[PDB]
Length: 107
Length: 108
Length: 119
Length: 105
Image (cartoon, rainbow over all chains, first blue to last red; front, side, top):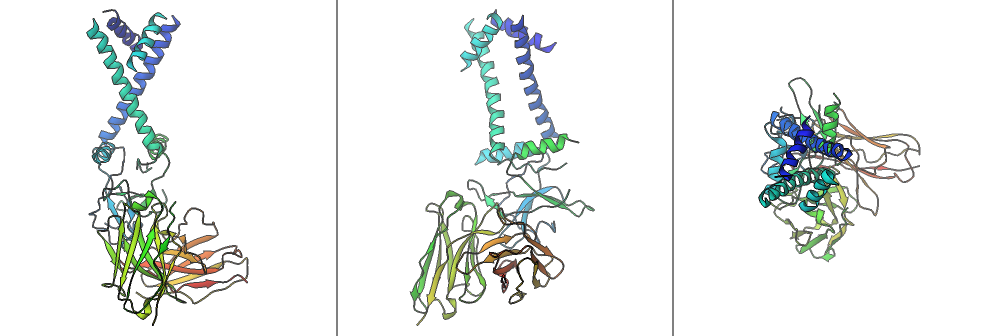
């Protein structure tokens, strides 16, 4: 139902059978892509999209390696060559993908 | 670029200027959205989208390296310690990390 | 990956100074920690110095603290260790190692420059 | 930090060697194993106690149990003959082991 309304709106903009089916199909594909984008945004907002923020250099470093998992929220991190311990940062629950992309664009 | 898409659409239909510009602007917005999603796909392809795959077993945590300067180190593993889980650390893949997280999330 | 070539080794009197240079080939040199590790003649490996990406953090082994200065430049992609006032026990073969992010340890190593302090 | 390895362990080709690396509290720390050959740069054989870099044959493996670590080499080939150093972190300075010489008889 929606694709016919969408192409009718486009026609109305234009004017002040197989082709119709193909137009409806491409509209369906476009709206499905938009719907999946909105679904990803919804998942990001709800917090179910762990994207790792870049680890700050000022990290105090833990008292042991990651496998000991000493200070836990689902952080992500890497082992520092300085003292063999690993500097870990929690994943931001609110907007992980968005915050990571904002940090990426800030550089 | 929008002109070609507009011509294609009007041909599909039949194979004042302000509203034509409006149609062109909507076309440009659609092209921008497609470009943004394609950019996301490309960045994931190059593997600088550190989406750690969760939702068992342990894994290696590698050294910390800084990406394109900035004093910030790209993570190498994703670690979680609940109060009774003994904690697990899974490395973030160099392959499609976002795609793999989405897949091994949608499996269950 | 990275091609590391050391240099600046030769005969020097005790108490002299040397400037060992590791000329890493590749921009990816900028991302990793680097380290100088010395294997003394007929002895085992001994850690000398470690440098982070920017040079804010410079770590030395207690034997050489206050005598060696590790440094790096990213424009030329080079790691220079300046040893000052060497002692008779500093003879060794110094290796340039890189802490690659895809390895988790000193995986990329250099040829190894033979220092020789003698009368 | 006293970190000790045997001076040398040698086996005939084929058997499996368990090179020990005894150090206090070594279970808490993570241990790397390097393979140094006379006249060649050291090769990182094991990192994070049990993990191998890309290209290292699956023969090599690592283990840790309490105040000791171990490098296990199976199917020792004629090339494996080398020196093997176990490295850890005291607090912030990396300490290497004495190094064990594995010889292929």
